[PDB]
């Protein structure tokens, strides 16, 4: 969806900025509270877990040739026991970590692609649980 892609792009842009990278590779109940709550959850999450998904990124070893199906299979790893608010946060951090790794690999073109994959994955596999458990309003309630 449009809002999903917007949420994803906001979180990724935020992580790249915060870590010294560019976010230009994208373009060329409210939404603000959700985005802010997500930026916060990610920071909180990354402060206690610093291994930045070494294993997962390894399994994927993303390149310009990687296909969505490969991405989807690696991420499912996070949801072997089903969806959680916490696992959703890890999902976003993972995407952020993937983007950073891509820039460090001189594969900045994958950033926008990664963003699309996350929006697709979020819409397909995550939103179902999210909507069943209070929607993003419940998310703000817990992470606001």
Image (cartoon, grey):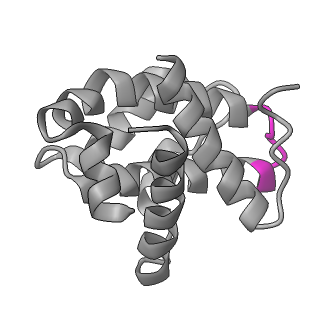
Does residue 53 appear anywhere in the picture?
Answer: no
At a point 28% along the width and 33% down the height, the residue shown is 126
Does residue 89 appear anywhere in the picture?
Answer: yes
Is-magenta flag for residue 42?
no
At a point 25% along the width and 53% down the height, the residue shown is 85
Looking at the picture, how far across and down is residue 118, in whole percent?
Answer: 48, 33
Residue reaching furthest bottom?
A: 48
At a point 44% along the width and 22% down the height, the residue shown is 120
Give the left or right position of residue 83, taking residue 92 as reference: left
Vertical placement of residue 40 versus 107, above or below: below
Q: Main secondary structure of the magenta part?
A: loop
Looking at the picture, how far across and down is residue 59, in whole percent?
Answer: 44, 48
Of residues 108 and 84, which is closer to you in this image? Answer: 84
Q: Which residues are magenta?
A: 103-109
Vertical placement of residue 10 versus 18, above or below: above
Residue reaching furthest front?
A: 29
At a point 24% along the width and 49% down the height, the residue shown is 138
Looking at the picture, how far across and down is residue 24, in whole percent?
Answer: 86, 39
């Amino acid at each position: 969806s449009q809002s999903n892609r917007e949420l994803v792009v906001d979180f990724l842009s935020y992580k790249l900025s915060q870590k010294g990278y560019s976010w230009s590779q994208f373009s060329d109940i409210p939404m603000a509270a959700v985005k802010q709550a997500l930026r916060e959850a990610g920071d909180e999450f990354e402060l206690r877990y610093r291994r930045a998904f070494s294993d997962l990124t390894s399994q994927l070893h993303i390149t310009p040739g990687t296909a969505y199906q490969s991405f989807e299979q690696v991420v499912n790893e996070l949801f072997r026991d089903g969806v959680n608010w916490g696992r959703i946060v890890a999902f976003f951090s993972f995407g952020g970590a993937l983007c950073v790794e891509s820039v460090d690999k001189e594969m900045q073109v994958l950033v926008s692609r990664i963003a699309s994959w996350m929006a697709t994955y979020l819409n397909d596999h995550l939103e179902p649980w999210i909507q069943e458990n209070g929607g993003w309003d419940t998310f703000v309630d817990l992470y606001g």
